[PDB]
Structure formats: C-alpha cells, structure tokens
Image (cartoon, rainbow over all chains, first blue to last red):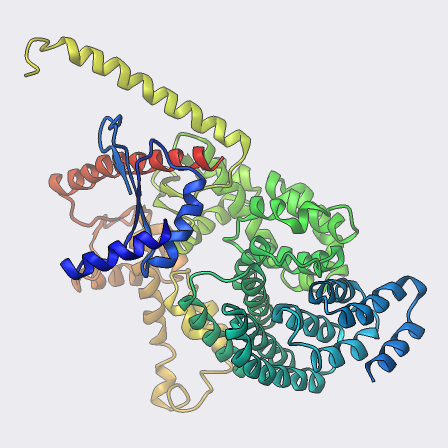
Length: 68
Length: 388
Length: 143
C-alpha cells in the first residue's frame, strides 16, 4: 500500500527529522528475484540506494542472522 | 506533398521492398503511431544499404517526428549517416535535430505526464564527437567524450544502446591513436553491453574482430582470451576466411607451442603489413604466456631457469633477461637468485578459468579440509574436562 | 622515447643507449652541444648505470658480481667502486665479497620483521574465505 509509506514517513519526519526513508527490510528466510522488483518500487522513494536488510527473524544462522 | 515523395521511393524500390513503403502512407493516415514506428524500424535496419533512405528519412525526421518515440527518430538518422561518406552532410543534420528535441519537450512532457527526452541528447553528442574524429579533429572529440562521461555518472542507469554508443566512439578514438591496450579493454565493454538493435551483422563482427585480435597479439599483458570466445563476436563465427589464419594464431598461443607459431607467422608476415613490422612483439608475448602458466599449475612456486629455458624454447641467456622484465611489468613478482639459477615467485597473476584448472582448485580445498578435521578431534580430547 | 626509458625499470644497456642518441642529441645544441658539455655525454654513463643498479638490487637478492659487470656494461674495477658509492650514500645496502664472486643485496631484517609479515598472511586468508561464502550464497538464488 504505496500511499501508506508516504504518510507514515510524513509523521516521523515531524517526530525527528534525522529519520528518512532508507529502504526496506525483508524477513527472509532467504533473498529472491522478487525482492529485485520490490527493490525497484522502494527506489523511487529513496534518494539513496535502498538498503535491503535481510533480517532472518528465526535466527537460524550460527553467527550473524542479519545480512546487509 | 508527402505522397509524391512516397511514389518516387516505390518506383525505385524492388517489388519486395514495396510493402514497407505502402505501410508508411496508410499507418500515418490511420494515426496508428505504434505501427508508424514499427514499419519504419524494419526499413532502416537493412534497407539503409540502399539510397532509398535519403529521401524517406530526412523528410520524415523533419516532419512527423513528434508522433513516434524520440529514440526511434535518432535511430534512423544514425542509419542514414552510417553509409553517408559526407561529413558536411552529417554535421548539418545533427545540429538541426537537436534544436527540434529542445522544442518538443515543452509540450510532450505535460501531455504524457512522464516521457524522457534526455536519450536523444547524449546520442547526438556521441555522433558529433565521432564525426570530428574521422575528420581528424581529435581535440574537439576528446573533450566531448569527457563531458558525456561526467553527465552519464549523474544518471543511475541508462539503456543498453546509450552506453554501447558511448563505448563505440571511444573505442574508435583509441585505435586511431594506436593505444592498443585501451582499444581492446573498451571493446570488451562494448560487446557485453551491446545494442539489441540488429544493425550488428556478421560482417560487422569480422571488421571488429581483426582489430581486437591484433591489439591483444602485440600486447605482453593481455590475457582475456577466455572472455573473447564467449562474446558474440567469435561465438557465432569462426568459419570465415579472416578467422582461419587469425584464429590459429590465437590457438597456438593458448597451447603454448612455439614450433607451430613460427610456421604460421612467416607466411602472415608478407600478407599482413602490421605483422611484418611488429615481429619482436609477437615472439615476446608467447614466451611470457607459457612461463606464467607453467608455474601456476604447479603447487611448487619455484622452478629453475633451465626448465623454463625448455618451456619457452629460448636459450638460458635470454630467459634470465625476460624474467627481469616480468618483474617490471608486475605480471610476476618474486626474487632472483643466480647462486642456484632459480626463480622463486611470491606472486602469480590469476590465469584464465578452464575446466582443467577448476579441478585442481577442488582438490586443494578438499586436502586442507582433512587437516582441519584431524586436528579439531585431537584438540577436543586433550583437555576434555575444561571447556567452561 | 628517451625520457620514459630512463624512468622505467627495464635494463638499459649503456653503449647501446649511447650509440642510438649519439649522432642526434649529443650534437643537439647547448646541453650537450657545448664544449664543456661534450663531457656531459660521457658523464651520462654514471647516470644510466646507477638507475639500473638501483632497480637490480631490488629484484635480485643474490647475483654473481661477474654477471653484473656485463649488464651494466662496465670495467669490473669501476663497477665495484660504484657499488661502494651507492652503499655509502645509503641509497642501497649491499654486502660485497671482494674477490668478485657474489654481490648480495641485503637490507636489514630482524626476527620481528619476518614474523610480522607472516602474521598478516594468516589473518588475510581467513577474511577472504569469509567474504567468498556470502557470494556463493548470492549466486545460488540468482540461478
């Protein structure tokens, strides 16, 4: 819901201006080729390169369960 | 008015090329701007050979441009001046088109709401640069390319056709100055990214393939043969006359056999005037290649000179000097001991990837993997009780 | 062509370089064409040989003295004078076996120095393999 991401951003810029849109997290478990498409939609918002933070919430990783 | 131009074109055209002409008149009328572009596109691709292009293009580019994609407008102009052997003509038509795009965007941007027109800008300038290189006004060309490069980096991404056209112009300038290494390196980038346009034909592969092969033969550091094969240029065609002798030089290098290499080159020295005068380079190149390869495959990282003497098929006096030069370039690094007549390397360039060499990689990491295993189990047992 | 030869580490054979530019630039005006400057072409010898000498210390840790006289193209008594000069100036550091058998280019090592290079080798390996593993992961999904 594209509109919602705009709206929420508006609120939080008022709370603290240092926060800006910087991309999107995925919960994994794994990266996909659909996440490429998804990236593209966030690219429009973002004036940086959108950061894809793969947080595995399950934490099956022996070390870091988070890749950037 | 326009119809009179269409009739002239049809009379000179072949019956087989009649239906392309007849499609332009009807589709324009029908205001199908999709088919207006499609019919046209087919025409410029191959009927650019014929002079048919002069009358149809220039008129259509100067009249009914607004309708079709801008990209499609500049693509035809490109085709017309390919075959054009006049530079006054070339320079004129470009300056004129540029002015037209500038106007066009005032309306079009709002109308569609979104529609790029910066595509056409860059391509125009790329064409203009090139015009100056062939005219051998090299200095003008240099600064236009530089400017394009800066502009381009502000954009995150451009079309395949845009970076293929930047690259093409740059590669032309480099072979003009006979900067062989830079010609070849920029030519690689060109192949990978190549226009989906089918202007590139088998004859255009061959033309490009003689220069690419010459630059790398006379080198002493170019070892991108594996990338070359896999690229369209040599992929589809190997079985022409240019690729009979020239490809055999190429093979002869790869197998590292100097006896064959010698045989071919003597014949090629009369026939080819580039190879006549660059004899010294051709022999140096083959020497460095066998040498860098022989040390690589061995897990031993020192080999005596005398064995290298055999490998390169040159006396031992000449091998010592060659190895001094290998360090200078930085293709190999190491130290030189003449108190045992050894070369002890500490650094070796990555060789090209081949099925055979991979197989060696697979062994090495299997082998190490057994040490790790053996050790961790022994280390577990000793001091079993303390691991708090 | 001249200037770029002398910067590059390629071996520069003295009477070959001398000969090639001899009928052109020795006769070229004031710098080499002057009466005093005729002797600035001869002095050019020292200059050439000392750049090669510098490069070769680097490359050869051990070379026979006999061989080194040939490459620089000099009299043997002279070359040795010139090895001493550059070691004195501390440009290079060398150890000379006087009968002329071996000339050994030796810069000071210590135990610590050698071990410090090795300590890095170990660490650099472990980092490389780590990075590769994430890149294996990437390619699996892309296929």
